[PDB]
Length: 49
Length: 319
Length: 32
Image 1 (cartoon, one colour):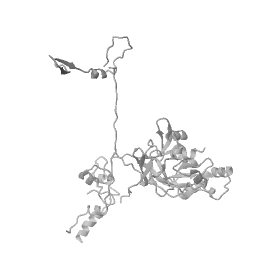
Image 2 (cartoon, one colour):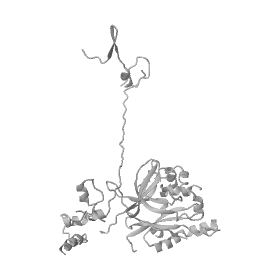
Image 3 (cartoon, chains in turn green, red, cyan):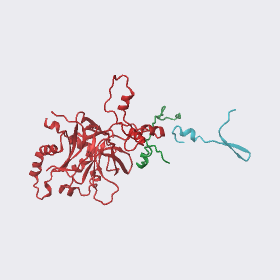
Image 4 (cartoon, helix red, strand yellow):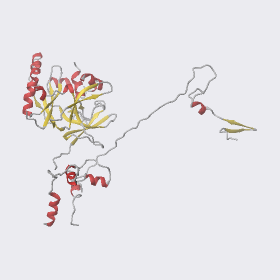
């Protein structure tokens, strides 16, 4: 909104701002390992205590 | 010996090489079990991990098939030495730095590899538009003039294959590249990746000659030594390495006598006319579809080799 | 009738009000 002046000025009309904001994209990651000795026994089925 | 039958039942059946379909409209579960390949990425739950079968040893199997998983080269580079506006599938070149311990390597796109050759003396407009200053690249090679002068620039640059992952860090960039194997992007929507080589640096060699059509048409990168500074050209051929050095000597036949006529090789080390190296294979049918690479200002033509199997080789000298 | 949102202080016998139009002027980007 604007204020109306009584004095002689070059007066401002109805201003309106259109502002946009864009998203960030953060790509978080790690790199864990798993030994092959602990994957062959995982996809097998034993019969021994 | 009865558990042996259960172990061999777990071990025997390969994926079906043939399957008698009746109609394509029915889409039976047998032909779905044929055509399905296990994935490589899934959500972080027990059901998704067990369904994609990532935990199977060696190769993926839910609870060998002619597919090889790729290997990834992990490279740390300075953020100034690389342009983050590069495409994904572009072949890079690690330069072997001369320090004993570095930590930070030095890679080069063929756009960035052009401006090491340009200074001291289209494609060059885009190259100078991407990287503003060559001096921030011409110190990565510490002694470029000597190394070009004694013709030992081919053994200090080894190819590394195309890029797949480029995180946009601020000081020290980490890029990932496929040094060997099936080039496929590591994105959560798994999208394909096309090896991009700029057009003026990529001259075809099948159509340069102008009937037995093979499948694997290799892509050869070629460093040559010119009086106008060295050049990095790219050659696509459907032939053997034995064929490729003969036909590349025939292709460079004017340039060798050009370099000989303007400069006499006064010493013994200036005889080598650079070297070549096989960058890997791709399909000879739908190879090298032409496309464009747009920066913010300009656009150069660039070839787009699709479905590349990267496989580097050592340098074979041209003479 | 309506509450007038303006703080009132006591100075002896008179209870004068204190109000700031700053916020009513900054939303027009004018010089106070």
